[PDB]
Image (cartoon, rainbow over all chains, first blue to last red; front, side, top):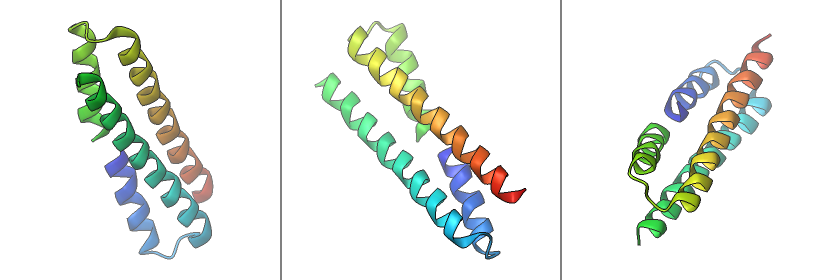
Length: 48
Length: 48
């Protein structure tokens, strides 16, 4: 789930795992959270 | 959440809500699921 992968990334960060690469993955993950918010808004627009 | 939206989109599809507009949202959500899977895969590749 987005929440699950988010936690997993946070757990690996606490271990200093591949910092630069993990930073890229975190930003990609947040992009999906933003995309999800966008879709929710598009759906609200459709209801309206 | 992604699960909450996914569920709602499926229910609106059973309800016949704005079909083409909803179908586009359904596919975008699937695209987000696929991106989420790709991130999990990229993470696993990093661990190798």
